[PDB]
Length: 535
Ligand SMILES: Nc1ncnc2c1ncn2[C@@H]1O[C@H](COP(=O)(O)OC(=O)c2ccccc2)[C@@H](O)[C@H]1O
Ligand SMILES: [Mg+2]
Image (cartoon, rainbow, N blue to C red; front, side, top):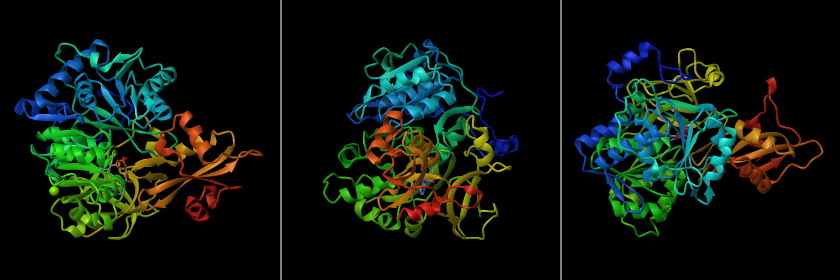
């Protein structure tokens, strides 16, 4: 019996291998803090952007108090809680308090709006929603009111700030209570995938596979008690949470330092002030920092490791990382679904510059296949399929999408196009999935098309990616105007999408209007040819 239904557990044969190999160590996710705080209670665990800092024993205690307060509210074993918080200490405490209460965090980003939040809350049948009050000029409590009208299961709303009619997250606090450990083979959290279908999809990560993700990534990244990790991406991003992210920093006893934004203004000062040794960024932020050192005077010398992932860093800026930033580059080809590829920190610089890494686990299995599903010859380009000790066997409550996306023997189809080199390192060559990668931000084309076509002037919509030198891809919305009406232009369509509740990173960069969409045989919209007609 598993505490949650709607997910697809590993076959018992694989489970026994991964336990025998020491990958699945049988420990709840919250135990990495409990254990580090018992051994190093007085070490500084967490620093925020203001300079406020907390020990391991203070983090562990506060998480115990907030787990107790959550239970006084009825948020307990197996309930799903949508979490949408900025890079604050409030997120870190709530993450471990939800785990210790038995609740399942459903992690969303600050940029997500009503469309994403309502669907994610509905799919998970979430019983609570955790928000800030106002962030980047948006009042998230308005969003929480709209979410509660569409999703009746939401009983509580916890606000990191002025809670209005809702519950203040700071008041969720009570004397610690003995709370039962969860089964380590159960789902610990739900991640939001970037998406390839009309509706976002949630990824269950179990305690055993996510601990191993964190533990093995910290080993390969040299994370130790002397690591000062700067959280530049959102705390809810798998990359900054667990690869090794903040959980890996806390697992080994380093210091987590929270950045409010990735701008040099904020990031470079925290690196100088806190003596940050490691961080992780997307390539657009990499290029910015690579530029900004020529007019910023911050001392960044404590930097030892810059991870760059989410999209492919080019070889020319990759080669600039050591001269400009004085640190080692690690390319990270990962996914919230599982498989992580890392360059090794002592790889020859050729491989750190030209490749996106090699798999994290000895039991990560890699297949590269052609259109006919057939394995390619060595060193040819095909679609990557993967199976392993921390890669999901199925999305959460998405059986139709599961039947298209995983092979009969359990291989997850990444939708990425790759080459495997003789050393085992991968080179990302492109994408088979219909998903735009806008500076690391993933845009499901089908989701956005369903949004655009709901506009009264749009009949059909085909969303196509465009190369961009600094963003990697931008978004073009190709529109067939509704019969005898005028399709909207770029600013009006963007305004319609915002009020419909679409995250701002999914707003099209460009609008193209045409009479019909190029079609292949079988009658599907040819977006390879649109990529040409719109050029
Ligand atoms: N270094 C890279 N080069 C080229 N493409 C990369 C890449 N890293 C991710 N990708 C692409 O993002 C997809 C997964 O994105 P996701 O938002 O779930 O998480 C990371 O994006 C993510 C999660 C954990 C660690 C790192 C990135 C991958 O399938 C791939 O298409
Ligand atoms: Mg340095």
